[PDB]
Each structure stands twice: as C-alpha cells, then as structure tokens.
Length: 236
Length: 240
Ligand SMILES: C[S@+](CC[C@H](N)C(=O)[O-])C[C@H]1O[C@@H](n2cnc3c(N)ncnc32)[C@H](O)[C@@H]1O
Ligand SMILES: C[S@+](CC[C@H](N)C(=O)[O-])C[C@H]1O[C@@H](n2cnc3c(N)ncnc32)[C@H](O)[C@@H]1O
Image (cartoon, rainbow over all chains, first blue to last red; front, side, top):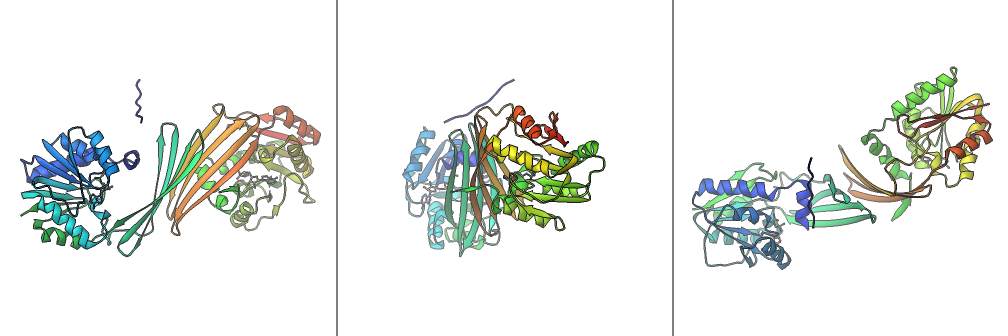
C-alpha cells in the first residue's frame, strides 16, 4: 500500500498528456554519442523551460541554452542550477565557441516565419558546431504529412480537477493553425480556455537544403518518440 | 453563454455520453417490458412520457404492438421521430397532455419527472399519466435519488472519440436540499470546426411519501423496486 502525489505552463500540460522530455533527451544523447562518442559540450537552442537540458546535463559535462523569451529564460535557469543560459535569437547569435552537439527540439525552429529565417537559424547552429559536430532538429510536420482539419482530444485527471481538451489543426499556405480549447471543472466551477498557436511548416527538401547550405550532411529518422521524426546531421 | 438543456446540440450528443459510461437503454427497456408483462400479461399499448430521443421506445417497439411517445423538447422529439419512423410521437407537457386514448402501460424513465420543480407539478404529471391508463394499467417511474457519495458537489468528465467527430464534456452538479444544479459544458470538434455549448439544469428530488401520495391521489396502488439496473430503483403502480 502506497500513494504518490505531486504539486505546485505549457510543459505541465504536455506532461499530463504523456510527453517525456527525459526519454527524448536520453535517446537524443545516445544518438549524439553514436556519431560522436567524445561529445562533451552541448547547446540546446530554443530550450524554453529547459526540461530537455535537465536530462542532458546528466549526460554531458558542459551544456548550455539559448532562448529569446526572457519569461522562459527565467524558468529554465530556476530548474537548471548549474547551467549557463544565453538570451538570443537563434537566427543571429554568436558565442565565439564550438559545441560537440546543437539540438533544436519540439518544433522550435518552426516558430520562425520564413524559409529565409529558418535557413539563417540552421546556419547559425552549424556555425557553433565543431567539425563532425552533431546537429539535431525535431521538425514540425511536412506539408505532405500534415493532415488538414485534424481534430485531437484528451481527458486528463489532475488533483482536484478534470480537464477536457479538443484541438483542431488547419493550414493556410505554409502556416498551420492549431486551435486548442480546454474545459476545466473543479470545486469552484467550470472554466473554459481557448488558445491558437501558429507554426510555419517546411518541407523535407527545405530542411535538407538548409543543412547543406550550412555545410552539414543530414539524415532523417522516421517516427521517433513524438511522431515528427528527427533530423541528425553532422558538420563536414 | 448558457442555454437550456435538450436543445438541438444536446440531442445530438446526449446518447453518446451515457452509453460511453455504460448505460444500456436496451437492457432497461427490456427489463421494464418484462415487468409490464408480469403485471399485465396482455399489454399491447404503451406510452413513454418524456421519451427524449426515444432510445427506450426503440426497444419497446420490438416488444409491444403499439407504442407512442410524449416529449416537450422538440430537438429531442426530432431525433426521436428520426429513429422511429412509423411511431406516433406527440409534442406535449407531462403536466397537462391529453391524447384522448388509454394505454396498457405508461413509462417515465431516467429521472424525467424530476425535471419538474415542485411537488404540485409532479402530482399533476403522475395524475395525467394515470388518466391515460386503462383499468389495471401499469405505470412505471424511475425516480431520482441522491447517490450515496454525492453529498455536496460532483465534477464529471467525458471524452468520446468518434470517426468524424470528437465530443468532450465537463459537468458539475451541486446539491442543496432536494435540488441539484446540473451544469454541463461540451466541446465538439469535427470536419466543420470546434463548437462549444453550455447548459444548466435543475433536478428536484421527491420523497417516497410524496410519490406514494401522488399515486394514491391519482387512483393508483404503488410499489417500489429496490436497486434495478440503474441504482435508483423503480416505482411500479397499477390503475384501479
Ligand atoms: C515550444 S518552443 C521550445 C521547445 C523546447 N525545447 C521544449 O521542448 O520545451 C518555444 C521557445 O522557442 C524559443 N524561440 C522561438 N523563436 C526563437 C528565436 N528566433 N530565437 C531563439 N529562441 C526562439 C522561444 O523563446 C520559446 O521559449
Ligand atoms: C434527458 S431525460 C430523457 C428521458 C428518456 N426517456 C431517456 O432515457 O432518454 C428527460 C427528458 O424529459 C423531458 N421533459 C422535461 N420536462 C418535461 C415536461 N414537463 N413534459 C414533457 N417532457 C419533459 C425533456 O425533453 C428530456 O428529454
């Protein structure tokens, strides 16, 4: 007989829906080490809450983060005691040092609006790679793969609350419109919440072209733990 | 924001929810039909009062030659006709309807009577239904009782994923006296988009003493069946 309980914002939500930043980071680290057994320096770009980095730190002596939103740069530092974090734009940063690996996960690069912007980002990351360094990038769905009008839904049971969520994803051009609507029922009442988020899709040929332009040989791992696959490139 | 219950949106999703939690209108109607035959072996004409979508009536029709329905919300009576092409269905109020005809049995199931607000209204309903009974006719009524655990408040949640639509529901019910305040909030996502609609309803309990008095006031000898397939038991009365 025993019981568990946790207590005390996007990350909590995806964790409740079943996402494991730890398993993802571990798998990513295994693959980085496959290509680069001596990897020691890692930079996570668009780290957000730094959940991935929490696990990367257990695997690489030195790890760093790059983040544009200072509200998230706050939370990451809090959860990441010994981690050097930099405020910056992925499209523009320069830190004067190389890394054995640069990661860009959970569709972070798809927060850029144009192919010209994504290619500048991919080139920046590649610039911070030492020779043979590994670039890892989790892309947002490929236009060919993107179901349109896709409707998702999940029911999460939290402490004191039941949460319903229905989503709908639509496209206009290359831009993807995810409409999320939550229902939160608890002691005080039922609250409704609605969100929309926009990610700009790129094609496999577009990523592959951006890698090559920045001197990296790319490969794509179908599926992976998220469903969106994984690019693993090396800077030749 | 809030609408009244049993509108068109509610009618579309109303059965999906209770079936997903394990309700079988078929088994209920079948059991009800068996008991009607116990008390009235020759029963042939049946009327379901507050039939809603007619889910019960669907199985009653396979068991009784002539079957009819009475329903106030036209959105529920619409789907009722849809599901029951050749069945005379009537728009009416439980408290006042008059169809000029008697039946061998009149049913009022799934706490339909407890959507009335006062004891006087239930007694008018119970008296109206009894007027539509032939001598020896059977009245069967599923009353609302408070679940053993529902002391103050309850929060429910449901997600059914169908092919072509997903339906989410968060509910909240609070109790005070004999009144339960039902707040339901739905999310339907489908080909066309994401729709939300919200409802509030009042369910009012009546006492065993009140039912027994309403039946007697209406010329009926009553009896109560413990438990039943829902948990709320079942009143079965006969028209002397
Ligand atoms: C959901 S993604 C973060 C993915 C993160 N690795 C995770 O899994 O939690 C959003 C983050 O990307 C960062 N980001 C977006 N555009 C950026 C840009 N141009 N330069 C740097 N960071 C950027 C923002 O700061 C934001 O915190
Ligand atoms: C949701 S339950 C439906 C019961 C139905 N037999 C079933 O199990 O599906 C309550 C129903 O009572 C009906 N109703 C409520 N008050 C009524 C009244 N005064 N007269 C007739 N029908 C009424 C509503 O239209 C609603 O469909």
